Image (cartoon, rainbow, N blue to C red):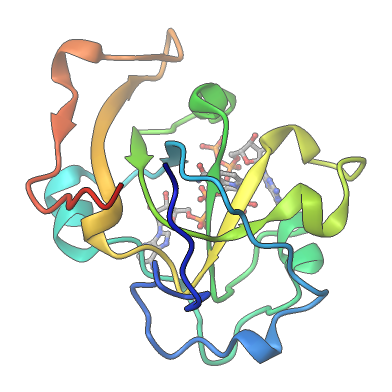
Length: 160
Ligand SMILES: NC(=O)C1=CN([C@@H]2O[C@H](COP(=O)(O)OP(=O)(O)OC[C@H]3O[C@@H](n4cnc5c(N)ncnc54)[C@H](O)[C@@H]3O)[C@@H](O)[C@H]2O)C=CC1
Ligand SMILES: Nc1nc2c(ncn2[C@@H]2O[C@H](COP(=O)(O)OP(=O)(O)O)[C@@H](O)[C@H]2O)c(=O)[nH]1
C-alpha cells in the first residue's frame, strides 16, 4: 500500500539538503496519504517548478524553531488536514500532494505547541513536481475550494 524508501529526501526538489543538520531528531512520516499545501502561487508556476525550499544552504534547520516562527528554511510545509487552507486569510490555492516521507512535525516536537492543529509534515528540500497531484483554487470570502476550477498536474507520476 505504501512503499518505504531509504532516501529520506526522495521527495525533495532541492537535492542539496543535508539531513544530518536536521534538529531535533526527526520522526519521519511512513504513510502515503494525500497531504495539502496552501500556496498563493498559481498552478502554471507550481506544476512547473515544484515546491522548492526557501533557504537550503543557510536557513533554519531546527524544525521546532521553524514551526514556531516562519523564517527562511530548508523545509516546505504541508498538512495532513485537507481543510487547513481555511485558516489562511488569502490561501490562493490548496495543492494536493502525494509524496513519500517528510518530517512528521507533531511526532517530532509534540502535539502541545502553538500551531499543533496544523498537523504539519515538513519536507526537507521541498517537494518535486512529480509528487503534486493537482490543486483547487480557494475562494477567500467563503474559505472554500472552487471545486469546478480544480486542475490536475500533468507532471504527476503515481508511485503507489
Ligand atoms: N502552506 C501550508 O499549507 C502549511 C503551512 N504551515 C505553516 O504555516 C505558516 C504559513 O505557511 P506558508 O504560507 O506556506 O509560508 P511560506 O513562507 O513557506 O510561503 C508563503 C508564500 O511564499 C511564497 N513562496 C513560498 N516558498 C517559495 C519559494 N521557494 N520561492 C518563491 N516563493 C515562495 C508563496 O507565495 C507562499 O504562499 C508557516 O509557519 C508554515 O510553516 C503548516 C502546515 C501547512
Ligand atoms: N506554524 C506557524 N504558523 C503560522 C505562523 N505565522 C502564521 N501562521 C499561521 O499560518 C496561517 C497563514 O498565516 P499567514 O502566513 O499569516 O498568511 P495569511 O493568513 O494568508 O495572511 C495562519 O493560520 C497563521 O496563524 C508561524 O510562524 N508558524
